[PDB]
Amino acid sequence: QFAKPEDAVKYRQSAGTLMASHFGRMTPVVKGQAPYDAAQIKANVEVLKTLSALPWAAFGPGTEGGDARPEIWSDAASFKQKQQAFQDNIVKLSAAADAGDLDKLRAAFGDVGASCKACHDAYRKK
Ligand code: HEC
Ligand SMILES: O=N[O-]
């Protein structure tokens, strides 16, 4: 769906912006600094699940640019493992939110954040 590589770059950066907002806005809730409303969190995690599926199709071959490292394309299999594992971590967060279970939500939130960071450390330029 991208006329030039620059359009794929703009798309995946905007998806990252929205993912950071929908993930990070739950930090005060998992810390107990803001109240826990199970329905509010269930709906927010639904939005995060949709968004978290979107970046990967915008790293098609030849779309190099932005702060993407070249290791994404020459090692297709390792990059795919990382995005699939990340989306699995999001399934655990969705199961916790759907159950209304704050203990499971805290643990799943930490695992999701670690997965964001592990990919950025390997595949995003400093
Ligand atoms: C690989 C398997 C990734 C996972 C998991 C996550 N991110 Fe990511 N992110 C990734 C790359 C390769 C890039 C660079 C894109 C480019 O072409 O520049 C990014 C970028 C971001 C950004 C910055 C967007 C911008 O302003 O330019 C943000 C804010 C971001 N990513 C957030 C984010 C969050 C919150 C994640 C998990 C919840 C997450 N990313 C996972 C690769 C990967
Ligand atoms: O949102 N980072 O792929």
Image: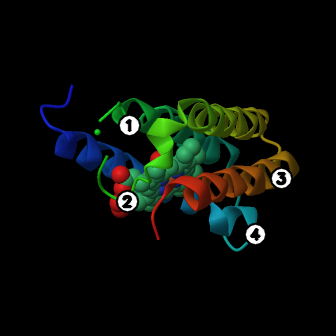
Q: Earlier in the sequence, mark 4 or mark 3?
A: 4
- Labels 3, 1: front one: 1
Q: Position of residue 13 (x, y in %)?
A: 34, 52
- Labels 2, 3: front one: 2
Spatial separation of the CA atoms under disc 2 and disc 3: 30 Å
User: Within 8 Å of ligand 1, the CB of disc 2?
Assistant: yes
Spatial separation of the CA atoms under disc 2 and disc 1: 12 Å
On the image, numbered disc 2 is attached to which residue? 67
Label 3: which secondary element: helix
Of 8 and 93, nearer the camera is 8
The tally of labels here is 4
- The amino acid type of the residue labelled 2 equals Asp
On the image, numbered disc 3 is attached to which residue? 107
On the image, numbered disc 1 is attached to which residue? 59
- The amino acid type of the residue labelled 1 equals Phe
The residue sitting at the top extreme is 1
Query: On screen, 20 above or below 87?
Result: below
Q: Is label 4 in contact with label 3 (beta carbons under 8 Å)?
A: no
